[PDB]
Length: 330
Image 1 (cartoon, one colour):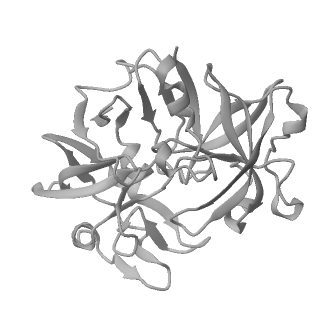
Image 2 (cartoon, rainbow, N blue to C red; image 1 turned 135 degrees about the vertical axis):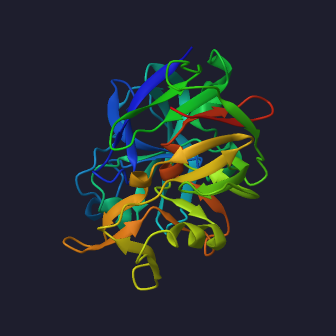
């Protein structure tokens, strides 16, 4: 089997991408944030505290003839940005782009933090990291991909995120028309539950490539590119007037600037992020200070190849017995 679904930016900045997902019988379609940095499939629901729902589409398990309470199971998750959600668990039929999993754990939110309530465009998350990170207790649950894997033509999924445009998540096959050149594969460590890999270095604009190992995670659920402070300082030093602002929370730059590209290494291959992908617009409406798309990871504990980096590539998440990641230009 295979599946193929379009993923669409939630706003003009590509802050996140939503993909329609069919849950239950008859189908209830919710727009979920596919997140290769977490491993829970959770949804706004008929059980979510009413004051914490503001425009999201909800899953109502009582209206699904295939829903079954997973008795005793609860979940609770906290994300790197400080947001969180928790609740109970149903199993139900879940389909993405024509690919169907029966008995998928659908984690129904009873509580969500304010950042989720305030984003009416995201109806939940669909985790695509390794199932060892799934938060369901007392019986940990498998991700959608883990449940589908055995049925897929090939045990892979691909992320092809658009710049200011829709893109595609495919399951079970690699669309050879969706990228240019060749795909370069690189080793993955699953020891922390993430799609963790080591970039071979970077360049700023037309500058020389610096060969240096940068361990980080491929994370579709994080907007920006978070790298070591040395790398980030070298980037922003090439933008006149750019500076790190403690009050804003990161590097800002004059909106009148033209940003240089940023290149990262994948083995001997190179992925170029155009400068325009690094512009996240005014810090507040009408401001001439703009927020940068490359930020320091120093306060995180891990480097994160988020959407800013991933949308410059066609990315293969290879879930074979020994997982690997592939990157191609496009």
